Image: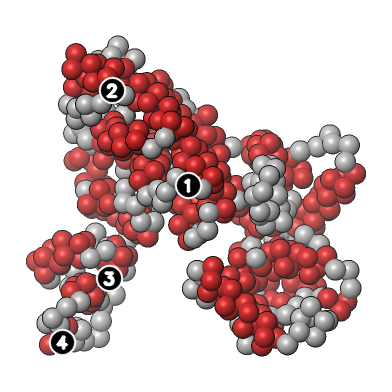
């Protein structure tokens, strides 16, 4: 829903990230588990997301690369506390560090990295889900 | 003059840096890369071994060595050589760049086909020059057909990479006034349509087989529009956008492989965004761009409402809200804004699907211009 909403923003840098995220998410186990249960309803997002989903023999798998030593990218005190100003890079760096091999068994996560890189409100929205999943 | 007149390259670099700063380019490299195709074509057109590719002045682009120059500009150097069948030179470039020549040829495929396909497309002319252009295109293409380079995998490469060829063909449009001449290709609209037809024989059906292509073409066009800070090439890219959108609308009732709703919404929102960020209305090219955007919006809205009877209820309110302020600009745009609004709300009461959409709409401003629109709104 968030990505479909942001597909119509004036800037051209979040639209490419959004379509990449749609293509990655809608080709996995959870993407189909979602489409089957959501196609029974009526919503314009069903028609808007039709092109980005494809029928492939093997559904996309996310590489669950295991870091040699986790807890190191998030133990920094400077990461967890920003300065007086410059909240955007603080939240972006925190979200990116949370996405650097730390937990996140969910497959739709680890696929929102470009959207987090290009947008800040998306980082603020997604951070609680990352913490909960970890 | 740098090559032979003896101009000192440092003074030339100083002047070029100052000029690129004046035009608003972040770096001189981007400014000189914007005209790289013309420079390389006119360099190779000088039939002399003194003016070969090695002797091309690369210091004017802030490149330290030949290797970095190739690293950065082989995407545009290779197609210019290949169309001349200088395959030994592309082999030498690959050897210098320590990359395989097959990879470079595959990565530069659409820019190669730009110089090949349109000459296949249009024939029957009495112009001899175009006849030798067609002959050169045919010989280059059949050389590429040979198994030694690209093998027989040209068909798979072509079918699996169509959007890039499509956008490269689109970016060569030049209808002809006082507009500056674009990059060398200079292909009018009809030859582009012939190229699409020729690709179809060997087009929108193939794209509809992978409905995500239209998104890629639209994204590329909008990206090249956004990176541009000028007005002339901005209007040019708007012309390409209008051409592609018109061709896409011509293929309605096919469904675009289920991609109709997304492309309709994307086009509507792109046009709305272009309209909203209007700098002013004092420059002629700005007025031409505004008129073109309004015409495209009117055409797409009319096509959607006529051949869908739906899919416009979710966009009617934003379109109306964007169009309302445009009436207080001048009569030239006022006439088209008013008749588009009249088409949307006045003569559309016969449709029950958008009856509720018009009912749940903001009232029109209480001015004389909106008198008929206000009366229709109140009645509905």
Chain under disc 2: B
**Could you give the CA–CA distance between mark 1 and mark 3, rounded to whole angstroms?**
57 Å
Chain under disc 3: A
Q: Residue at x 81, y 37 (%)?
A: B123
Residue placed furthest toward the left? A132
Disc 1 is placed on an element classified as loop
Residue A83: x %, y % from top left: 15, 83
Which labelled disc corresponds to residue B282?
A: 1
Sequence-wise first label, 4 or 3: 3
Is residue B63 placed above or below B258 in the rendered structure? below
Residue at mark 4 = A78
Closest to the observer, B361 or A88: B361
**Could you give the CA–CA distance between mark 2 and mark 4, rounded to whole angstroms?**
62 Å
Residue at mark 3 = A64
Query: Are dots 4 and 3 in contact, CB under 8 Å?
Result: no
Residue B378: x %, y % from top left: 18, 17
């Amino acid at each position: 829903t968030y990505l479909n909403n942001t597909l119509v923003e004036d800037c051209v840098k979040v639209r490419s990230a959004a379509v990449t995220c749609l293509k990655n998410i809608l080709a996995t186990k959870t993407g189909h588990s979602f489409w089957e249960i959501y196609k029974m309803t009526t919503d314009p997002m069903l028609a808007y997301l039709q092109p980005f989903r494809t029928s492939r023999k093997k559904f996309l798998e996310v590489p669950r690369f295991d870091k040699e030593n986790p807890f190191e990218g998030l133990d920094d005190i400077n990461l967890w506390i920003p300065l007086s100003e410059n909240h955007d890079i603080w939240i972006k760096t925190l979200t990116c560090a949370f996405l650097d091999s730390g937990g996140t068994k969910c497959e739709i996560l680890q696929l929102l990295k470009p959207m987090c890189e290009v947008k800040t409100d998306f980082c603020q929205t997604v951070l609680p889900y990352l913490i909960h999943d970890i | 003059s740098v090559k032979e007149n003896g101009l000192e390259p440092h003074l030339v670099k100083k002047v070029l840096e100052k000029v690129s700063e004046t035009f608003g380019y972040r770096r001189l490299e981007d400014f000189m890369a914007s005209h790289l195709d013309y420079l390389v074509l006119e360099w190779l057109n000088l039939q002399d071994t003194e003016y070969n590719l090695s002797s091309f002045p690369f210091i004017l682009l802030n490149y330290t060595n030949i290797e970095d120059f190739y690293r950065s500009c082989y995407k545009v150097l290779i197609p210019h050589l290949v169309i001349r069948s200088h395959f030994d030179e592309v082999k030498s470039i690959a050897n210098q760049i320590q990359e395989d020549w097959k990879s470079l040829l595959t990565d530069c495929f659409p820019k190669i086909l730009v110089n090949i396909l349109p000459y296949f497309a249009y024939e029957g002319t009495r112009d001899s020059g175009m006849a030798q252009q067609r002959e050169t295109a045919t010989k280059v293409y059949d050389m590429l057909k040979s198994e030694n380079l690209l093998g027989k995998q040209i068909d798979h490469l072509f079918i699996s990479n169509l959007p890039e060829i499509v956008v490269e063909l689109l970016m060569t449009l030049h209808e002809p006034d006082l507009d500056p001449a674009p990059n060398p290709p200079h292909f009018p609209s009809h030859v582009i349509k012939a190229t699409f037809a020729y690709i179809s024989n060997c087009i929108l059906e193939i794209l509809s087989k992978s409905p995500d292509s239209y998104q890629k073409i639209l994204l590329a066009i909008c990206e090249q529009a956004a990176e541009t800070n000028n007005v002339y090439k901005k209007h040019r890219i708007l012309k390409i956008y209008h051409l592609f959108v018109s061709l896409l609308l011509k293929d309605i009732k096919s469904g675009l492989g289920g991609a109709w709703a997304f492309v309709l919404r994307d086009v509507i929102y792109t046009l709305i965004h272009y309209i909203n960020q209007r700098p002013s209305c004092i420059m002629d090219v700005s007025l031409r761009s505004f008129s073109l955007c309004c015409d495209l919006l009117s055409q797409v809205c009319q096509t959607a409402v006529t051949y869908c009877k739906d899919a416009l209820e979710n966009h009617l309110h934003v379109i109306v809200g964007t169009l309302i302020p445009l009436v207080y600009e001048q009569v030239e745009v006022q006439k088209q804004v008013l008749d588009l609004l009249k088409y949307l709300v006045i003569d559309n009461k016969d449709n029950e699907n958008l009856y509720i959409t018009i009912k749940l709409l903001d009232p029109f401003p209480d001015h004389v211009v909106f008198k008929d629109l206000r009366i229709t709104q109140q009645k509905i």
